[PDB]
Image 1 (cartoon, each protein chain N blue to C red):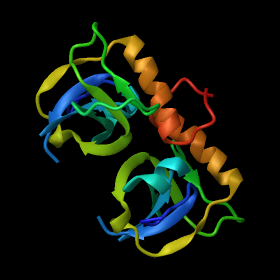
Image 2 (spheres, helix red, strand yellow):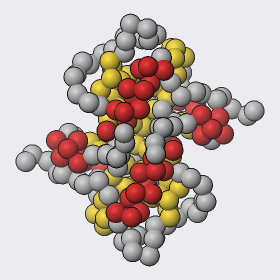
Image 3 (cartoon, rainbow over the protein chains, first blue to last red):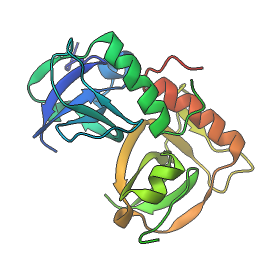
Image 4 (cartoon, helix red, strand yellow):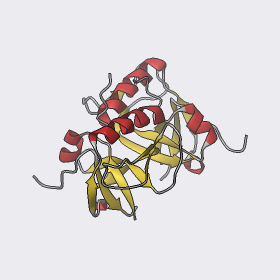
Length: 104
Length: 104
């Protein structure tokens, strides 16, 4: 083990400072130098690609699944918590919609 | 119509110069200020998240679906062509794998 191993569903403060949710798969997150993440925002919108955090999640606000970026592990700052499996399932659908995938 | 309307499957030269393939949905690409894209590279790898261009595609090399980024429309340069529907279907699967989605 030679570098940090972030996990899908975790949220980190990053200055590229705002919070970013890790959406890349855990094998890539452990073994490579970077991750893919989506932006958390206080901005409120009611559209298919935005997911509001719920009363069981560690953070308030909204996930913008349209804003997908690759972050270096060196750019990951404070660990803020882990999104619930329920909220992550909504995020999976939102990501699929953002990227024009034929699923579900 | 107030700004460019790139399409999913199109490839543009961008300096953030290398080619990037548009993977965001066409509604977002027409109506918003940015797009999501994945990197084209000459680097060869034989892994689930890399997709080789085929003999019917407009470009040679490989799509790295692990490297997903949000590009401003202002950052899009020369239009290089459009990836075939066959190759795009492979890209859809690669993107799903990169982002740990439960599909297909």
